[PDB]
Image 1 (cartoon, each protein chain N blue to C red):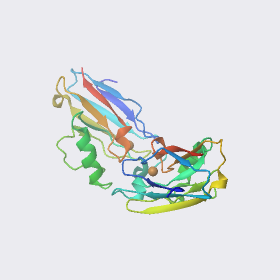
Image 2 (cartoon, rainbow over the protein chains, first blue to last red):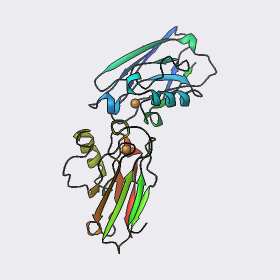
Image 3 (tube, rainbow over the protein chains, first blue to last red):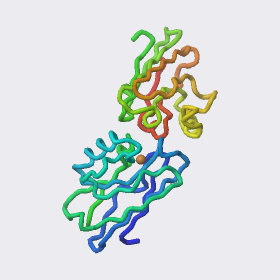
Length: 128
Length: 128
Ligand SMILES: [Cu+2]
Ligand SMILES: [Cu+2]
């Protein structure tokens, strides 16, 4: 805990939070994502993807085009700071990343890239 | 147009209209649904479903429980007044229903029951 947060993507197409702050003392930060619900990945999969607020749009749009087999992420997208995989219900994944990749004074956004989901499944992240 | 309306459901989970006025001189009313875009039915499928504003929530919950193969509509649901099938991009479907099944002063909603889409794809239908 302290440098980790548990996140949930449900069958209603929402995340349980919309603002995560990363404490400057953390060397690494972990996101544990679970998918409560009953629906399969192909109709209601979720991932936790991080980028800057300004890159988000590019990542969601190139992710959408890559398709379900690339977990709707462009392979080696260098706008992507960190991402989990695309999980279906009852599945779980965790991503740990370097806090050094964040810089204080920049807005980040986490979001899901499964088509249409970022309209509700998104939140701000900031290093503080 | 005369006793019919054309409706579109696109890749960003939006219907092109959000209010339909059926007119009382119509014995029947037709809604012609189409889906602009490129995503298939299992990612961005849409249907047009009508029920009272009061029954929409159960129709949505039971719908989501029916599965993709049942087009996310509970078969022979008593509360659905008219519905198209679920369609992906490039697919088209229509429904004609009799205007005697709507009464004056009752509030009706049209909506899409594909998981997560109702919160964003819905509108009111009025007998005038
Ligand atoms: Cu999602
Ligand atoms: Cu829909």
